Image (cartoon, coloured by chain):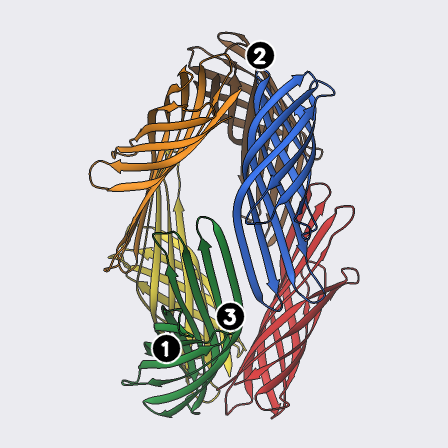
Chain colours: A brown, B orange, C blue, D green, E yellow, F red
Amino acid sequence: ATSTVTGGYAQSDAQGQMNKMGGFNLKYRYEEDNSPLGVIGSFTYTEKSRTASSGDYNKNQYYGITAGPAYRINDWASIYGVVGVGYGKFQTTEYPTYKNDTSDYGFSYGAGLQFNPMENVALDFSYEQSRIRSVDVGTWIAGVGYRF
Amino acid sequence: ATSTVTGGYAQSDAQGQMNKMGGFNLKYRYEEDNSPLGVIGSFTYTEKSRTASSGDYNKNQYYGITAGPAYRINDWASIYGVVGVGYGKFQTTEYPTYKNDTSDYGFSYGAGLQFNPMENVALDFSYEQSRIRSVDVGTWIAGVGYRF
Amino acid sequence: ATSTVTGGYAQSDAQGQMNKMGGFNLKYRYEEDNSPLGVIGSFTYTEKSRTASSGDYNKNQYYGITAGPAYRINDWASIYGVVGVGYGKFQTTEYPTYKNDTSDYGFSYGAGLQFNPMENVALDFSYEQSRIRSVDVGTWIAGVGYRF
Amino acid sequence: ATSTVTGGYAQSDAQGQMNKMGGFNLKYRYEEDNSPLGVIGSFTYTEKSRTASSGDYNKNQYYGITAGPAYRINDWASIYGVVGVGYGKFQTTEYPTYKNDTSDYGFSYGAGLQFNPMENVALDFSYEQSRIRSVDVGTWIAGVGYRF
Amino acid sequence: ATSTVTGGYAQSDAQGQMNKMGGFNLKYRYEEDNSPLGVIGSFTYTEKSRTASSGDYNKNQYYGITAGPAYRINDWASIYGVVGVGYGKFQTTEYPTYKNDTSDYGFSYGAGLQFNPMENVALDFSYEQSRIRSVDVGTWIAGVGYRF
Amino acid sequence: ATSTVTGGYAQSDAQGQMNKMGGFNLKYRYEEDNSPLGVIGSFTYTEKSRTASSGDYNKNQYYGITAGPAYRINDWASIYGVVGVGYGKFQTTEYPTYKNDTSDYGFSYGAGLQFNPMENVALDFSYEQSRIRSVDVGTWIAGVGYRF
């Protein structure tokens, strides 16, 4: 009966050192008109590239694909929790021509909320966490969209 | 609870001169068994290519991605309105080898109806309009499908 | 209100001779909290490759894309029926360099069931059948997933 | 010591029925300043596509890659003979969606001449023949270029 | 009988405003042991990208493919002249999503020299000029390589 | 004045452990009619893939691109030496989804001979050696071809 589609800026940060990996998030939620329980799917992508004067180049990409239950608390607030899979791809080119690329999948989970300040508008805020090998990647998301 | 999937022929026409740009549309609608309000997403794609004896070639493609509320009026009729984004890509090859390609996005909106002459069948008719720079693109769609 | 996502192993077998074509299936089902009728979409892909000492190589791929109604019988059992389209691609390289590739679409249908031994878990079992030219392809699927 | 590069129009014709398959040829020849014997390599590509009102579509492509000795007879005339490999790719889409593609290699040979009406100019005329399965493909070529 | 292969840095500059477009050049020359006249082919590629704080992005690429006679003056010096074709591709993305891409071919010519300070070593210096529409692109090249 | 084109089987072996990496080589040589010194360019490619019951997969590819002087000793024998660059790409997928890919370039050199048992035929035998990081890759080649 109702769908909400939001998009915004996402920012990841891993165990200390990889700095801030920037990007975006999209979410699609569905609700019934006569039940407070629905579902929400999320797509997050962040990245960062570090080049140089030397020549050494490195590029990190993070993908987060999650889904879970969403619960409407009142006409202007809802909360949700999501689980799924995180994917990271690290590229490194060591001057002048050595190239080494590694990728792996890991478990991902998250939780968020949505507010409806106007009935057809949504403000979305969530946090997502992924493990991937032994590196804990945490991402914060602030989005906006429409409920139709 | 119910979904309806329809597909058909789409035909676009822009501010006068680009002639008839032909193609297709697909829509996916979802309804609850106990609410008349649901949602519908639409995908439209049209195109046209003009070649020659000279050599000058041009190709225009239009993409329309929209979504919105659908309201069931009775067992055989429903109406919906959609909003989203239109995308146009104009290619021109000026003989013998000059190539110039331009693309942009714009706001899109539309409205339609669906009839169910039999309970598991749907007849879909809609009109979509996109702006894209200063060119108003209007597309008419007639589709058929199944409700399951 | 509820979604169930399952994945598993799929195994196809065609009119006698193509042996067992192995692969996978994914399904996405949606249910309302206050109606036993919902919908389920299915994606199946199987394949097989036969090489040699001689050199003759052949590769067969099968894709099945179906959707239909799902009906919840009680808290732990549901049944569904699906219809859609099957696609097959047969590749053959006759030594030392002749290559012949053929592909076509046909009608597909299937039926299955799902059990929920725990409320957020699903066990999925279905059978899918496709025609494609004059070759009847039948595929068996056993999957597992989560309901959220 | 000297090179000649020519390009022109090529036209193939196979055992009767495939009509005229149109396209192009490029050749690169090399000569020594103090020997009349040199070498020449050739690249030929032709094609034809037949569409419809019905829907049946077919596309034929021919590639010819050959090389051999070139002999300069006087300051304005040379003759050459080439051998190598021909490649043909036949595509057929039988309405509404059956697709069948076949390709194979075969022996190719050819012979030609070049005239130099001015010392830095060349006029090239050759004929190429390929077998490929049991289909004899014969191609005529008329090119022009520069000797530097 | 002898070949020389050199590579180096290339830098283009067009009618005033496009600044310095950086890149590389490769050349392959061939000589006979008993004639001072031979041939040389050249491949040049340069580029430049300008991004921003605003968002407007532009990317210019230049390709130069030329060939011509090379004349050995003594054991350590040779001169050559080349002619061929220049290709330029200008990309521009006007924020937030307008994209306009244009490309064309034009005549190219150049001239250079090579020194052999040691018999198996070469130092290459040349200048290339291309027109392309009405924009005169001039490129300077300094390369090094081996004669074998 | 004369060219010789040969192709054959190549087999690489690295410092002990990577076993036998199989593949091919192509060479193009050019000779003048009145000098025993000419040039020859070589392209070598070998590979090996190791899969499993477990799931761990690894794939190694080796590319060798070399060129150098060729000297004709008599009407039936010639010797040559080549230098250039070797490239290796090692892929490893650690079950169930970790992927790690590394590539680098290194110096390559080789030496060979060619016999002409008949004037338009050639038998080619060479050995190529590449370093690439700290791994010494040695490849043996036996080819056949035509002199025209």
Instruction: Check disc 1 and report its element: helix, strand or loop.
Output: strand
Residue bearing the label numbered 3: E145
Left or right for D59, reference C60: left
Residue at figure coordinates x 62%, y 26% from the top left: C80
Amino acid found under the numbered disc labelled 2: Asn
Which is nearer the eye, C36 or F137? C36
Q: Is residue D67 above or below residue E99?
A: below
Output the chain of dot 3. E
Please rate how many residues cluster around mark 1, counting C-alpha atoms within 10 Å: few if below 14, some from 14 to 19, many from 20.
some
Q: Residue at x 37, y 24 (%)?
A: B83
Cα gap from disc 2 to disc 3, whole angstroms? 78 Å
* Visible residue check, residue E117: no
On the image, numbered disc 1 is attached to which residue?
Answer: D140
Q: State whether residue D25 is above or below residue F92.
A: below
The amino acid marked with disc number 3 is: Gly
Q: Which residue is mark 2?
A: C34
Residues D1 and C55: in front is C55
Helix or strand or loop: what does disc 2 sit on? loop
Whether the residues at callouts 1 and 3 have beta carbons within 8 Å, the answer is no
* Visible residue check, residue F141: yes
Q: Amino acid at mark 1?
A: Trp
Q: Chain of mark 2?
A: C
Residue C24 sits in which quadrant?
Answer: top right
Residue E87 placement (x, y as % from top left) = 35, 59
Q: Residue furthest top?
A: A74
Q: Residues within 10 Å of mark 2 (few under 14, many from 20)?
A: some
Cβ atoms at labels 2 and 3 below 8 Å apart: no
Identify the residue at image location x=46%, y=79%: E30
